Image (cartoon, coloured by chain):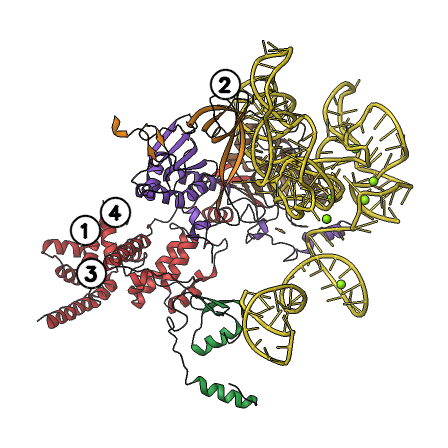
RNA sequence: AUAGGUUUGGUCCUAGCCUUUCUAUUAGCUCUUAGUAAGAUUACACAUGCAAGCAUCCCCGUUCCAGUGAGUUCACCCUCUAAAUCACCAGAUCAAAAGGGACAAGCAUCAAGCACGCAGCAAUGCAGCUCAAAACGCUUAGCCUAGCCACACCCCCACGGGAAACAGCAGU
């Protein structure tokens, strides 16, 4: 489908079945459908912990670097995954959400103790 | 220095000890069968074909390397404590770039505590299996390697099968690989089944293990009983090479031992069953003279 | 066997058969020595030598005759007329 | 070099010289038959610009692709005449030949 | 039975059994040969046997035959650069002709196997997708992972139909 | 196909039809639970609700996603090179238009098409071009499925007209 504009984005294509999410980190034209055509599959992400309590993320780091050099963008979930991996700095919203969670749990603990 | 398992002299000695039984090496495999093909061959053509099969058997019996147990991986890359408590599950990030040796891939783990460490050896092997699956290897360790099942396979005398499963499932430096190989070698020693590994690629490893543990008495006894006295002599020479400052080697050097003399010297020194070895050698020599004269 | 009665026909046929026995060479006592393509009148029989445990994948009549002969493993395709006698 | 014509080099037979400075060339390619798995000749027609008009019906010619089509159908130029009709010169010996017979014996030189 | 003499020539196995894969430079191959003469037997058998294999291995090279046009048989390759390679095949057998053309204008085994490895690069073992492209279709096929809900139902606590009940 | 039934008074051969196998839709009868996948027959007409916002105003988006299969060799490779991304440029990536090639089925009781070519800077000249190796034509069909092509009420298009549009979701 001849698209106007748009750009390559490294993003998560959601496969899996109902209640069984699974993601394919793909470099795809941003205008293409979420689970539709893609240029290259750069990795995968299993949000469900496995038998060992691990969320398996596979990153084709060489090709991710190649596409970032070619000018691909990064969806925020992929940015946060890379930050977790250490490939990028931790996302500002990762840090801020951690801080918000800390404040919320501090409130909870303080209220529980007061009670 | 002391020679290693991969040195050329040791490789030659161990290959000669192993032997190249074509029937055993190319024993028919219980697998999906296709109808056979038939060729008309002269005597020269048949000799050429058997020579090619011998070369193929050498390739097939190429010994696996003996590698020291890998050291545990403990290396923390980052300590981002801000992530502490944000997630309750580990993330395992794998570099699945195609053109990278699996011992060079970066497989890191982000823990719930915010620690970005390097994946342990077990996790590394598990993830490499997950993403670059190998034929014959399973992610979850097969239960056959539990002692209760390993002893069943030993009782059936499937030591070669146990070693094959171990070599398919674990890495040569794996703790489990080394443990299972040593256990199989020990059981072969106890039950005197050293012929189960002859003409297989694991005979070299078994011999190396016995030599390094100074327990080649049983193997010498079996070889003399089976008349492979050249193999026994090479085994004793290898033992002396790997223990140059040993009582038996020094005694042989003091005397002039160049064969059955070497085996007798080993029987008299550095042998837990020296009397038995001497009896076996005496019986072999007596039979040799009997059917020679 | 020809007879006005079915049992007499059976007796005649099975008694005459034993005086007209072939001997079939079986490779390793389970199959034939090589692939055989033949045409008897308008019936083509294409028999393939097969490995052990393959079974008899043949016309049912060929399966019966092979069980009698002693062949365990063989493939067989019958083209043309399927006349049982031919 | 960067020609937009698919067939860069094609050897064909001239089947018509009725157009000025153009030679109609029949180029045959072996095309596998998917069912019979046998190679048959698939012939296509190419117009080859011939500036000098030196092509005769029956000549085997080598056509080179023009950098761009110079006409609605003339995408090739007459690169060479490999076998002039009736005036073949055996490439092996460079002597004129009439079919399988040497018009000049190669021993002549 | 298969029609024609030597019906093995009409099998994919035979066609792929050819070992000549021309360099990218070769564009045309004209095979001039004589239908008669004991010296042209090699060229005759070449056209009868190996031309199908050469064409199968090189689908984009125009192979064109010529009959009784010159006293002696010969191949002539027209390359992309404009060069012409003449290969006089008189007195050679078809096997010798194949070896010669492979030596002078065919890709070497090293180049062919590097091209094979380059092709292999595309099919990454770690990619998940349809069977036509990937070894596995979903991570659920990997042991130790949460299995496919179709085969093994998920825990009610992991099903949103009951997370909703809990949140209600 | 490992075949089987069926012509005859009978046998042999050829031969069509049918059985046995696996799917999909529909219908009859029957039907307990759980998980998952799939889900109008109709390119016929649509009540009703929602499906495109964001943002310190400018811009950007509503050209995407989602839908359908009416039409249908616009999809694939090469050349060239727009628009777009790479904070600017960079060549890299992606990819239009244009040029070259390849590319569905049936009917030859569709066998001729009727200007379908070339050269020249132009003026103009030559009379050529496709086709029984299937041109021209009629009919049928979404396709080569990580998806692609085409359409988007009809007049192929949509200035204009007919007319007032769910082939977006739920629904009629
Ligand atoms: S196909 Fe993988 S979860 Fe269902
Ligand atoms: Mg029903
Ligand atoms: Mg009619
Ligand atoms: Mg239609
Ligand atoms: Mg409508
Ligand atoms: Mg319209
Ligand atoms: Mg609707």
Shown in yellow, the chain is F
**Residue displayed at 20% across by 51% down:** B241
* Label 4 close to label 1 by CB (< 8 Å): no
**Chain for mark 4?**
B
Q: What residue does disc 4 label?
A: B7
Q: Is residue F144 left or right of residue E24?
A: right
CA distance separating discs 2 and 1:
94 Å
Q: Where's residue B71, x and y in %?
A: 39, 46
Task: Out of D103 and B48, give the one closest to the viewer.
Answer: D103
Q: Where's residue E132, x and y in %?
A: 56, 47
Shown in orange, the chain is D
Q: Colour of chain E?
A: purple
**Chain for mark 2?**
D
Shown in brown, the chain is A
CA distance separating discs 2 and 4:
75 Å
Q: Colour of chain C?
A: green
Of helix, strand and loop, which one carries label 2?
A: loop
Q: Is residue F154 above or below residue C65?
A: above
Q: What residue does disc 1 label?
A: B245
Q: Colour of chain B?
A: red
Nearest to the eye among marks 2 and 3: give it: 2
Of helix, strand and loop, which one carries label 3?
A: helix
């Amino acid at each position: 489908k001849a698209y106007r504009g748009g750009h390559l984005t490294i993003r998560l294509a959601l496969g899996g079945c109902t209640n069984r999410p699974f993601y394919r980190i793909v470099a795809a034209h941003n205008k293409c459908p979420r689970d539709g055509r893609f240029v290259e599959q750069l990795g995968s992400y299993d949000p469900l912990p496995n038998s060992h309590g691990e969320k398996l993320v596979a990153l084709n780091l060489d090709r991710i670097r190649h596409w970032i050099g070619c000018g691909a963008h990064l969806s925020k979930p992929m940015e946060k995954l890379l930050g977790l991996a250490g490939f990028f700095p931790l996302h500002p919203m990762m840090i801020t959400n951690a801080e918000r969670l800390r404040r919320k749990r501090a409130r909870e603990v303080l209220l529980a103790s007061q009670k | 220095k002391k020679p290693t398992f991969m040195d050329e002299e040791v490789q030659s000695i161990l290959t000669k000890m192993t032997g190249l039984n074509l029937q055993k090496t190319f024993k028919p495999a219980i697998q999906e069968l296709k109808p056979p093909t038939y060729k008309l061959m002269t005597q020269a053509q048949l000799e050429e074909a058997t020579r090619q099969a011998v070369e193929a058997a050498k390739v097939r019996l190429k010994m696996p390397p003996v590698l020291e147990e890998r050291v545990p991986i403990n290396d923390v890359l980052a300590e981002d404590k801000i992530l502490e408590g944000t997630e309750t599950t580990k993330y395992v990030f794998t570099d699945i770039s195609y053109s990278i040796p699996h011992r060079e891939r970066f497989i890191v783990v982000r823990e719930p505590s915010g620690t970005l460490r390097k994946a342990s050896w077990e996790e590394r092997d598990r993830m490499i299996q997950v993403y670059f699956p190998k034929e014959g290897r399973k992610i979850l360790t097969p239960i056959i390697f539990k002692e209760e099942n390993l002893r069943t396979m030993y009782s059936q005398d499937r030591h070669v099968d146990v070693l094959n499963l171990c070599f398919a499932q674990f890495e040569p430096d794996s703790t489990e690989y080394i443990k299972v190989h040593h256990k199989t070698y020990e059981d072969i020693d106890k039950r005197g089944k050293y012929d189960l590994l002859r003409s297989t690629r694991y005979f070299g490893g078994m011999v190396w293990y016995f030599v390094n543990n100074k327990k080649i008495d049983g193997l010498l006894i079996d070889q003399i009983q089976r008349d492979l006295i050249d193999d026994a002599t090479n085994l004793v020479q290898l033992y002396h090479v790997l223990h140059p400052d040993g009582q038996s080697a020094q005694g042989a050097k003091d005397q002039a031992a160049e064969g059955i003399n070497l085996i007798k010297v080993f029987a008299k020194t550095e042998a837990q069953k020296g009397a038995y070895i001497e009896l076996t050698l005496q019986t072999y020599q007596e039979a040799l003279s009997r059917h020679s004269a | 066997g020809k007879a006005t009665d079915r049992m007499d026909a059976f007796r005649k046929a099975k008694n005459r058969a034993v005086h007209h026995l072939h001997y079939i060479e079986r490779y390793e006592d389970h199959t034939i020595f090589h692939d055989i393509s033949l045409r008897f009148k308008r019936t083509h029989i294409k028999m393939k030598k097969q490995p052990k445990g393959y079974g008899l994948r043949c016309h049912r009549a060929i399966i019966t005759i092979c069980r009698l002969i002693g062949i365990k493993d063989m493939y067989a395709k019958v083209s043309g007329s399927i006349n049982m006698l031919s | 070099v960067r020609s937009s014509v698919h067939a860069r080099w094609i050897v064909g037979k001239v089947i018509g010289t009725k157009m000025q400075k153009t030679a109609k060339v029949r180029v045959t390619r072996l095309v596998l038959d998917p069912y019979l798995l046998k190679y048959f000749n698939k012939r296509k027609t190419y117009f080859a610009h011939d500036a000098l008009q030196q092509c005769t019906v029956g000549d085997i010619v080598l056509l080179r692709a023009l950098p761009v089509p110079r006409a609605k159908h003339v995408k090739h130029e007459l690169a060479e005449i490999v076998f002039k009709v009736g005036k073949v010169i055996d490439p092996v010996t460079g002597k004129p030949c009439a079919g399988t017979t040497y018009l000049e014996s190669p021993l002549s030189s | 039975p298969m029609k024609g003499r030597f019906p093995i020539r009409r099998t994919l196995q035979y066609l792929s059994q050819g070992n000549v894969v021309f360099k990218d430079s070769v564009k045309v191959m004209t095979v001039n040969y004589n239908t008669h003469g004991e010296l042209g037997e090699g060229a005759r058998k070449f056209v009868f046997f190996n031309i199908p294999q050469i064409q199968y291995k090189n689908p984009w090279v125009q192979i064109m035959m010529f009959k009784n046009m010159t006293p002696s048989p010969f191949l002539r390759f027209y390359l992309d650069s404009g060069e012409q390679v003449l290969v006089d095949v008189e007195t050679k057998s078809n096997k010798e002709i194949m070896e010669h053309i492979r030596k002078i204008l065919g890709k070497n085994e090293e180049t062919l196997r590097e091209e094979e490895e380059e092709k292999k690069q595309l099919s990454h073992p770690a990619n998940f997708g349809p069977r036509k492209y990937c070894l596995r279709e979903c991570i659920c096929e990997v042991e130790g992972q949460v299995p496919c809900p179709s085969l093994v139902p998920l825990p009610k606590e992991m099903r949103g139909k009951y997370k909703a009940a809990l949140k209600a």
